[PDB]
Image: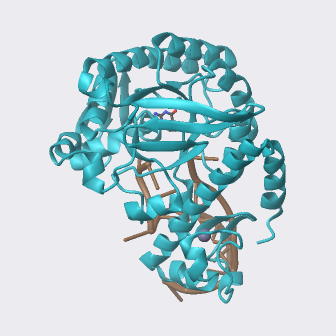
Amino acid sequence: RPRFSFSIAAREGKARTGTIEMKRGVIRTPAFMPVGTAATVKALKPETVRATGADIILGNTYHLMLRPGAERIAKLGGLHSFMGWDRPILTDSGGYQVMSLSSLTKQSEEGVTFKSHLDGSRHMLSPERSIEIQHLLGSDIVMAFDECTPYPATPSRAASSMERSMRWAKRSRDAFDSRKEQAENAALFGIQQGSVFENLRQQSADALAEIGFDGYAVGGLAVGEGQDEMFRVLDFSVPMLPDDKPHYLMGVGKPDDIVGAVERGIDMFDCVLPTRSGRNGQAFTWDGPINIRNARFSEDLKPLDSECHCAVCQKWSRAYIHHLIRAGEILGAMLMTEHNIAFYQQLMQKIRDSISEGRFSQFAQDFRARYFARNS
RNA sequence: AGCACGGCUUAAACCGUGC
Ligand SMILES: Nc1nc2cc[nH]c2c(=O)[nH]1
Ligand SMILES: [Zn+2]
């Protein structure tokens, strides 16, 4: 079985569908990877996650590092064994926390010093350390250590941040390659930065391509610049990346975001939207989002979504789920999440099939229509 | 507490607005 083999089977405009073959499994693309930060996809058993259609879930480096600890998971047999998910797992470097936890952070050329957001203890997360942790966890797709540049950002900050990241990228590549045990079984992705300035984006892309990575991700987006700006940056950023390699857009969920991103060449997505919203009561459907807490659902026997093939939608009504979330019942979170994730998978199935039939561009158009119409 | 809603792009079974 191959280590990492990306193959495009169909194309349409910038969009394309295919698969990534890895030792632990195959990953159909475009793909959506559910987020399982602390060694768990919130409120779901691994089998449930797999049931929705996911081929790969994602774990977080910074968080697992703190709890239950990298070395400890390594000792317990690795992340896969630990949480009960044997298919490929992608671990994020922690470069996202560098931003979301800025307040508790202290940056330096060596790496970023984090103050445990739960222990107060100090921790040095350098490119090398980030890669060692990912090795200890035994992830299949390793992410380079980077700094998800905050937004807005002056061309100056965005440039220094990006350049330090590219240097961090090289260090990551070296850390990865130092362990043959790792380099022979995992895959390494680099992350492109540069905020919303294309000259910077190009520059970052070139550094990345020079070092050489199994896959290239685009970071720094969906961080407050809005969909218009995002799609605009993607317009020129994705083409700067190696066409024969997979393109990964980090932290991007929200039905229409994904569809547009795919129209621009993205192959992979990861986002907390479906799981967090599921927990808060927000369900995603072919007719836009719907807040199940709303009064109009107290006696609505219909399922969350009319088309949805998901297990929740085959059995329970909006009325039951309404009651649940309102009551504070955990089953409520469970049901909501399973649905949002199966829907995200069904949406990905659709996006893949349309590209195969050469009628994706259309599918996108019909999608927004119905979605933004909100007749659920 | 509760009600009517909103937000969410893992320090979030959360946070906010109005009664
Ligand atoms: N490492 C990393 N993770 C994420 C997640 C979302 N955006 C980013 C990013 O720019 N870098
Ligand atoms: Zn469903």
Residue lying farthest to the front in this orientation: A1
Evaluate whether residue A95 shows in this view.
yes
Residue nearest the observer in this picture, A150 or A216: A216
* Image quadrant, ligand 2: bottom right
Give coordinates of residue A213: x percent, y percent.
47, 20
Residue lying farthest to the top in this orientation: A210
Residue lying farthest to the bottom in this orientation: A299
Q: Is residue A16 above or below residue A205?
A: below
Quadrant in the picture for residue A173: top left
Looking at the rendering, in which quadrant would you find the N terminus of chain A?
Answer: top left
Chain letter corresponding to the colour brown: B
Q: Residue at x 77, y 45 (%)?
A: A357
Quadrant in the picture for residue A170: top left
Q: Residue at x 56, y 16 (%)?
A: A204
Q: Residue at x 81, y 70 (%)?
A: A375
Total marks placed: 0
Judged left or right of residue A236, residue A340 is: left
Residue nearest the observer in this picture, A108 or A97: A97
- Chain A: drawing colour: cyan
Judged left or right of residue A122, residue A321 is: right
Q: Is residue A368 above or below residue A18?
A: below
Q: Is residue A102 above or below residue A254?
A: above
Residue nearest the observer in this picture, A225 or A52: A52
Give coordinates of residue A166: x percent, y percent.
47, 16
Q: Residue at x 36, y 21 (%)?
A: A172
Looking at the rendering, in which quadrant would you find the C terminus of chain A?
Answer: bottom right
Evaluate whether residue A143 shows in this view.
no
Give coordinates of residue A100: x percent, y percent.
46, 41
Residue nearest the observer in this picture, A154 or A263: A263
Give coordinates of residue A242: x percent, y percent.
60, 19
